Image 1: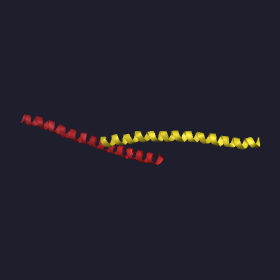
Image 2 (image 1 turned 45 degrees about the vertical axis):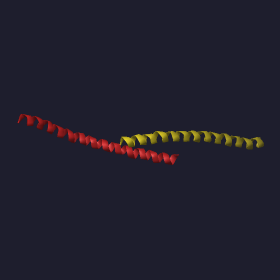
Image 3 (image 1 turned 60 degrees about the vertical axis):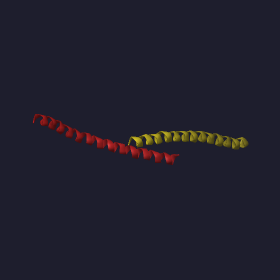
Image 4 (image 1 turned 180 degrees about the vertical axis):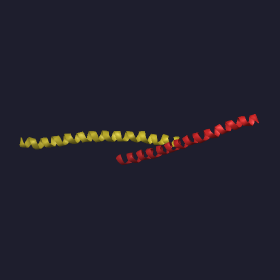
Length: 49
Length: 50
């Protein structure tokens, strides 16, 4: 188990990273949708003003 | 992406706050212009009555 425990810590470090890679990706994807939404809102509100 | 989001968010907030300012200005315009209209409507009939 000492040999498997070491490799299994990494197997968790990798899997844990993968979950942060996924979440951080979609966070950017959501962070960029507010760009097109609020920048377009900025435009329409500047022509309106 | 976080920093430039705050920049555009603030830009939208600043510009929309100005739209509210011009809405408040028109509101007062409507109030002031309506009293001018009311006075002009009474002068219109007073010019006719004379």
